Image (cartoon, rainbow, N blue to C red):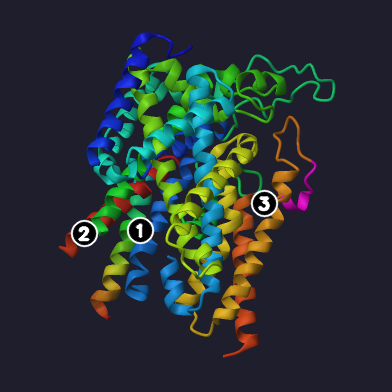
Amino acid sequence: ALIDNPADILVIAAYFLLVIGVGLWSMSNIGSGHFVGLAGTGAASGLAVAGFEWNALFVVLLLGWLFAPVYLMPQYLRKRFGGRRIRLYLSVLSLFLYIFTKISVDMFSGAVFIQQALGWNIYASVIALLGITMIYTVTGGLAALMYTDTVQTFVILGGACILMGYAFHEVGGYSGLFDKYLGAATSLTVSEDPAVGNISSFCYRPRPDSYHLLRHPVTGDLPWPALLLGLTIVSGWYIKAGCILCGYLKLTPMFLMVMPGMISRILYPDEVACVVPEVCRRVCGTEVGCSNIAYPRLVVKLMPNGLRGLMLAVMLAALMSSLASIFNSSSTLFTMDIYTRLRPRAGDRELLLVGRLWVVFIVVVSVAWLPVVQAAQGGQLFDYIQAVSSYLAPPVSAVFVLALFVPRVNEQGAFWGLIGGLLMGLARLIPEFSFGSGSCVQPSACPAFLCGVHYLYFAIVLFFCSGLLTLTVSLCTAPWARVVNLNALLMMAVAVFLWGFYA
Amino acid sequence: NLQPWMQGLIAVAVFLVLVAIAFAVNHFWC
């Protein structure tokens, strides 16, 4: 369809052929998942999505620098608490989060790229994605990894700049974008379903606060207090010059994805900003909302004939590398952390067969989960990822932090607090997945107690309550560096300048 | 109604003040 022209397929085939050739010859920070989620949330809600990454850095480096002299992830818990129950439970959370926020989302972004590059169904898309993933893995893709990773991040970002200009040239430049966006919505706001009826203007017009990082703290998409605190909590679970470069590349996404995500809504309002349920289905595959098509739609309908194929190939290659790496990590974790514990005999070949069968099992589970991903948190990938992280990680972060700071905590108390935090998190994961989330068009029947609060304020609540549980149970039961610092503060100043500019 | 660059410069100045405080505290006592 979009790439039906010979040139796009030629570049895609050439790129994949070179990737496989290097993989045979053997014998990063940003993937396609973020390139999809950030752009989708930028199209849907404005630019407060970029209020995550920048904030994350201003926390990460702080907790990367203000914790080093005092602390010097799971391995620390292993030394501090000992035993094996906490090891097994942390491995279980790691596997579940890999399935939910690293595997399901990676395949979903893959199906949201092949869907808008060819038009295939979600399953027809992930089937091809996983077939090519298997080809990549069986050809020694992981054997190269770091070898052919830098080059990827030297094009996927670089090419993402080529799109940036191509996106910013079709909106009359940077100044032009900031007038067009507020005045860009759908022309189809009438639904044939009698129950839906006419669609209100609140959730088909772009938000009034689409240009401010600090949204309303009570009625905002990304409340600033929730933003700050929830992100500093979640970032705990998810050399120094490496961190400085990571921050440099972490500042850009606002200009590279979020804003070109904002451009999608104004070049393609009917598709990216669809509000009518059945209209989204014919566009997307789901009737909850489809900003997630923001970046892939922009890539396929904006990039030239020859560079669109290159962008698709690079996105798919990075997604393939991420998926293969996470499959390998999950298999290794399962067959060296949990299954081995269940079977101490340590069979010569069982530890490998069980790894491959686990790989197949998680592939199946994530394929079954894909429908939930495509219709999670109003159809926004970034919101779903951060919601799952807010539901699962904050308890682990609380246990880690109170272990680092408080020496009166107990391993048994730590484990009980961790199970309490997981149970608390499943009181919003399960109910806000089985009952759905829904957009303003079709609000879900979820009780106001559960879905009323933003997932970041739930991160705050769950972190604090999990910490309190851990502490009470533990008590109750039983008894050139100068140059690096200068560059770090320069980067921090630049980041706060960017925050103030878009505050 | 401060311009965006006013807000950016204000943030930079505030952070530089905080950095000066954090440098003076350890300049005075460990």
- The relative height of residue A63 versus residue A440 in the rendered view (above or below) is below
Can you see residue A180? no
Q: Which residues are magenta?
A: A445-450
Image quadrant holding the C terminus of chain B, namely: bottom left
Residue kind at label 3, given as amino acid type = Leu
Task: Write down the chain letter for disc 3.
Answer: A
Query: Quadrant location of residue A391?
Result: bottom right
- Judging from the image, mark 1 belongs to the subunit labelled A
Label 2 to label 3: alpha-carbon separation: 41 Å
Q: Position of residue A258 (x, y in %)?
A: 45, 34
Q: Is residue A227 left or right of residue A310?
A: right
Name which residue type carries label 1.
Answer: Leu
Q: Neighbour class for label 3 at 10 Å: few (<14), some, many (≥20)?
A: some
Q: Secondary structure at mark 3?
A: helix
Residue B19's place in the image compared with A390, above or below, is below
The residue pinned by badge 3 equals A429
* Residue type, numbered disc 2: Val
Q: What residue is shown with label 2?
A: A484
| Position in image of residue A451 (x %, y %) | 72, 48
Q: Earlier in the sequence, mark 2 or mark 3?
A: 3
Specify few, some or many for label 2: CA neighbours under 10 Å numbering under 14, 14-19, or 20 or more.
some
Q: Which mark is residue A61?
A: 1
Q: Is residue A169 above or below residue A233?
A: above
Q: Are marks 1 and 3 on the same chain?
A: yes
